Image 1: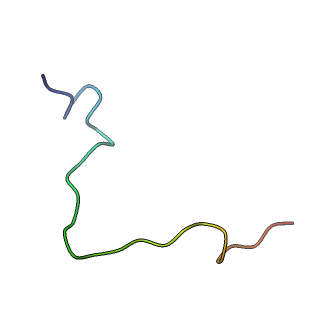
Image 2 (image 1 turned 60 degrees about the horizontal axis):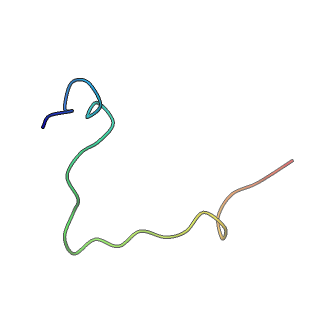
Length: 30
């Protein structure tokens, strides 16, 4: 049913029209 409080604290709605990139092009590693 719910999570918002319990398991939904991190889980939220998705944005339509906005695209996300992968974490392999940008980011430094030592």
